[PDB]
Image 1 (cartoon, rainbow, N blue to C red):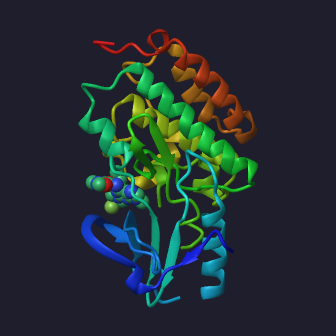
Image 2 (image 1 turned 30 degrees about the vertical axis):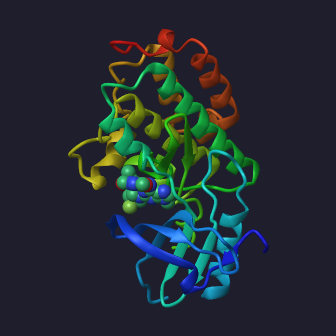
Amino acid sequence: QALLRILKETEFKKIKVLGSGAFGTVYKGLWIPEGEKVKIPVAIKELREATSANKEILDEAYVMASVDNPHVCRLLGICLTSTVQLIMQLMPFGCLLDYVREHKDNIGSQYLLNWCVQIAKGMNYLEDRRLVHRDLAARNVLVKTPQHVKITDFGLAKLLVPIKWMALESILHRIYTHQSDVWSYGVTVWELMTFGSKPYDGIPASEISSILEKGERLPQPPICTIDVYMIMRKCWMIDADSRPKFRELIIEFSKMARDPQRYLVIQGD
Ligand SMILES: *CCC(=O)N[C@@H]1CN(c2nc(Nc3cn(C)nc3OC)c3ncn(C)c3n2)C[C@H]1F
């Protein structure tokens, strides 16, 4: 339990709002641990107040605090009052979804393929721990530096619907496995390769199941060669066991990262 710090209310201060939504509020703030001589920049995520067991909350937070990988965000500390407040390291460049949209003209093939490797490394770490993420998406990848991204919000779903990132078996039967995480990974890569386009844009969530049942899939991004699109398509196979494994995705995307211009055709790159 020494991985999870229980923070007093005086030990952290919210300074600036970073974002707000149905989940709650995320702040940029300071962590001032008592009996220490340092003030640490952190993000503070205050979940929306709920009418619903503390023992199971701490137990899940202990798991979130136990993740130890350069490409998965760790839970630094927690503060339980009428609300749940999660403290973690501040990722100054924000979410990868906003980043690829803001830098669509200045992102080369090497950055994109390196991100695919790092996301697959983080997800493979979780699979080795027998942990399922359930909400992998570009909005849930954070940018520590342009060459270092981390998967965020692990365990938050269990602590508490992204239809367009979900595998068909998850939509129809609410089944979540590592192989359904692979489907979400495929959609995430598609978000990256389109510089942040919305998947199935304008299509209501209730229609997605019938799109997948008919055999339709997200279209090939303009910059993607057929080798990269084949990986995305394999992530979206109906048979979950036929999808790639995260360990295989690391190998194949690391191979492409060694000659990135061969696999992504980007103007000016
Ligand atoms: C794209 C998804 C999204 O917009 N999420 C918002 C922002 N969130 C968030 N942001 C950061 N870093 C950051 C973002 N901005 C605009 N400035 C900074 O730092 C200066 C972050 N670091 C750690 N964690 C958990 C973060 N979350 C979540 C939504 F509010």
